Image (spheres, coloured by chain):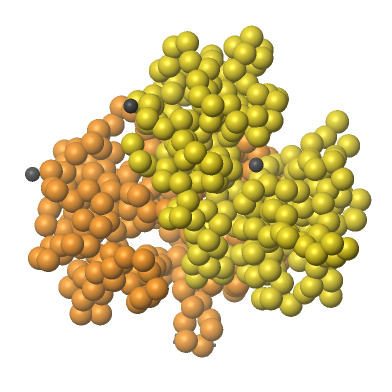
Chain colours: A orange, B yellow
Amino acid sequence: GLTLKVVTVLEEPFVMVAENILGQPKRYKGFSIDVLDALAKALGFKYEIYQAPDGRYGHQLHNTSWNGMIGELISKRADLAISAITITPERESVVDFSKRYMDYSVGILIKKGTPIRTFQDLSKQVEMSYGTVRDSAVYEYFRAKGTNPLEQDSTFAELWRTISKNGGADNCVSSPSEGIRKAKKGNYAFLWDVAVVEYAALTDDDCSVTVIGNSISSKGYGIALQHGSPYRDLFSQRILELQDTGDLDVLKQKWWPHMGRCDLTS
Amino acid sequence: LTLKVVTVLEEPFVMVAENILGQPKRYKGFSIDVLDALAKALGFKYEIYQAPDGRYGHQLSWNGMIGELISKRADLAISAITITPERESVVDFSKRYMDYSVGILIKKGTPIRTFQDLSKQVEMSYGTVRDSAVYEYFRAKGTNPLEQDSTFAELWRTISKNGGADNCVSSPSEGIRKAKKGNYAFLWDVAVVEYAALTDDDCSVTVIGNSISSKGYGIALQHGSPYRDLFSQRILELQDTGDLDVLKQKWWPHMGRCDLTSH
Ligand SMILES: *[C@@H]1O[C@H](CO)[C@@H](O)[C@H](O)[C@H]1NC(C)=O
Ligand SMILES: [Ca+2]
Ligand SMILES: [Ca+2]
Ligand SMILES: [Ca+2]
Ligand SMILES: [Ca+2]
Ligand SMILES: [Ca+2]
Ligand SMILES: [Ca+2]
Ligand SMILES: [Ca+2]
Ligand SMILES: [Cl-]
Ligand SMILES: [Cl-]
């Protein structure tokens, strides 16, 4: 029957590999998979998932083309893209996002037991390396806030001076997995999606790391569809219903356990 | 192009501005400034009118602003309208231009600093507007066995005492008035009670938030409107540049007004 092609990128606990037995297609699991499954059921479609061949969310290149999942949508190789995709104006100009199914903000992952408790505390650091994924939306977030003397505090300017040192070479990482691994080794603080670093801290074998939030949320996570897709408004309606009934809250408790895991209190 | 805009008064989203006798009513506020930025960005003019029953809208068909859009007397509706699935099924909302959540309005100087602390109260009156969406939110959360902390169950036990008659109020203005006179905490739209606290004549109240947002505020357009996606795109741009945050600081200003954190 009606089958949608879904492009994704691995991001814990939004989209993870579940099993891949030889001969069988790869299977996936996670919070975004469960939201997608609820939509598939309600709207009566099937789907097939593939990972973005370049592994990127996607951004705009100099000739106005896009790579990543965004590019897959523009080219119509994918009908929808889902993982932990932030709804931004640049991306919405070329694809069509559903209304959000979760809020987004940036957090800090750092080993427990330090005097750093806030973004402001991190910005005061003189010797400490900290950073984000180079070439990411989070890097571009700190560029924007850091190069804006119109902010009310030097916090973002100071954070940007460390993050962007040597064009991002010294203090940034290639992937969230590298940032998480470095934060656990100590002497590094990793700045990334708070939901991603919270999951990493909750599942740390040694319960050795904690997350600093406090970022005000102004953006959400969405399902990206093709420009002009008829499914965009249908998805939004059902997402709103999932939120109103409490079904989304249950799925969040499933992947970010309120209890049973590491205690994140430093 | 001129769009018909329907609204309802809600400080500081939409407020009456001063107008010369005989001149049409003027409006000002956070939502008005968002509307103005959309007009300038997209290049339209507009005329505003007030909903005849001063209601947002609910069904049993739709009244309030939702009804004006359904009937097509309005091209769009804006004030402090929350994006809900029941409303989105009959009209078309922009993506949100601000987050919504429920807060606590309470007199300064108590040991209550969180929703959990409020839920621990014995013999204290606290509540919300009777038969409101907020009441229904606390019903749903408070009766759900899958909640991981007893906080919501305990809040519901007090809010719904005697079918909601003992501890709930008839309107937000009454809830605000009761919290200011004491021996009551009022649970309502955090942006609304924050503004009430900032402008309290006696700078006597504070607001407890510490709640992830449940919903967004949106611009409601007609079902099938050609403008909805355009509005969403420009709203996202206004958020990303910080323009909306500047507008929020402008309409919920903190210096010159009451200090909400003096204790
Ligand atoms: C756009 O730029 C990218 C990166 O250089 C390139 O791979 C792609 O072929 C270009 N496409 C054009 C000219 O349409
Ligand atoms: Ca779009
Ligand atoms: Ca120590
Ligand atoms: Ca693990
Ligand atoms: Ca449409
Ligand atoms: Ca309201
Ligand atoms: Ca609709
Ligand atoms: Ca006291
Ligand atoms: Cl929204
Ligand atoms: Cl939308």
Residue B48 rendering spot, x and y as whole percentages: 81, 60
Residue A216 rendering spot, x and y as whole percentages: 42, 53
Residue shown at the point (25%, 33%) measured from the top left: A263
Which is nearer the eye, A69 or A125?
A: A125
Location of residue A181 (image quadrant): bottom left
Left or right of residue A36: residue A175: left
Residue B188 visible to an observer of this rendering: yes
Residue A23 visible to an observer of this rendering: no
Which is nearer the eye, A124 or B203?
A: B203
Q: Is residue B99 above or below residue A261?
A: below
Location of residue B193 (image quadrant): top right
Which is nearer the eye, B245 or A198?
A: B245
Q: Is residue A246 above or below residue A174?
A: above
Marker count (numbered): 0
Left or right of residue A60: residue A189: left
Residue shown at the point (71%, 72%) measured from the top left: B39
